[PDB]
Structures are given as C-alpha cells and as structure tokens.
Image 1 (cartoon, helix red, strand yellow):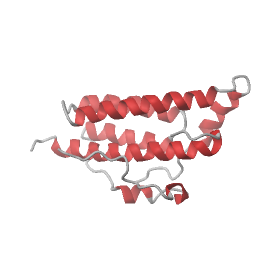
Image 2 (cartoon, rainbow, N blue to C red):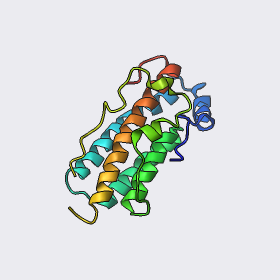
Image 3 (spheres, rainbow, N blue to C red):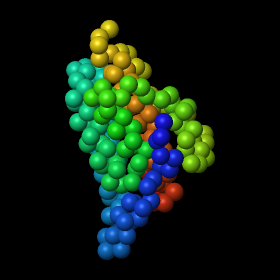
Length: 163
C-alpha cells in the first residue's frame, strides 16, 4: 500500500540531529533507546497474538510504537503500526504481502544479502476476530522487517553496526 518509499523522514531526523552540537551522543542515544523499546513491544505484541489475543492491547501497543518511531522519523515502521491499530479497531480489513511492500522501497540495495523472512514468527492462529489477529500477525512480521532495515540504514550514518 501507500507505505512511504523512504525508510527515514530526514526533515524530522535532521532536527533531532541538529541538537547533537551540544550533546555528542544525543541522537544516537535516542536511536539506541528506541531499539530496545521496539524489541520489547514486538515481544509484548507477540505474547498477545499467542495468548490473550486482545485487539485493544494490540491497538495500544501499536499506538506506543507509532509515536516513538514517528518521532525519530522512522516512517515505514510508523505506517505499519498505524495499520496494526486500524486492524485492531476493525476499521481496515486487509494487509499487503511482504513483496508488495518491500517493492515500494526507494532504494532496494538495502536488502542485498539479507533474507526478508529472517525475523518472522510462524502465524499459528475459528473466531470472528480470527482474521484480524492473522492480519495483525502479518503486520508484525512486516514491522520486524522494517525495524531491521531501519537499523541497517541508520548504521550508514552512525558509523557502527546498529544491529
């Protein structure tokens, strides 16, 4: 879908970076804070898919990660979280396949050598909500991929391997 083609919204990130002048490890410090939050919420979302299967929970978790990511200019992660929310509210009723989404990327050189299904959890989910939980579970595996690309991409600029 209309996922943004650029991994990073530089007009937002440049403004965070501007403040690195008086604080050397500032922007990198936010990024590294985000990388831990993201990993934690992905696991909390995965715990719900496999357990309570509460669509309000997956809405709130999608809400949290959408604010964090959107703040650092990580706009493809934010878009997927927005879908996780709308899917949990049954206001949207489908989610694209990985290939369709990966194909919108401004520069696909960033997926050289990596296996776009590396980080997938098997979707083991029958109920009226069953289809929304399956599509959230698809959106999460796309979120994990977008997370990784965000890390690879930020490494170019922070001169360290951010994953």
